[PDB]
Length: 31
Ligand SMILES: [Zn+2]
Image 1 (cartoon, rainbow, N blue to C red):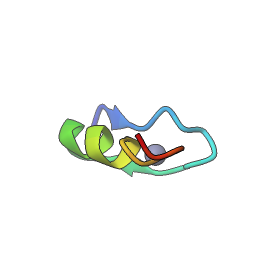
Image 2: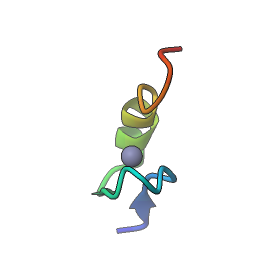
Image 3: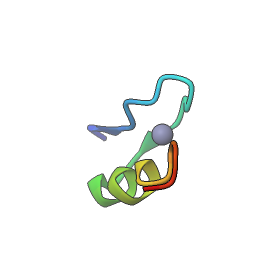
């Protein structure tokens, strides 16, 4: 699965691109 978050500290792979969008959406700060 070519879906991995860029957050190194995160250390978690994904199966859907949408996940990273929303998950990363709150990886830091708040936005
Ligand atoms: Zn992540």
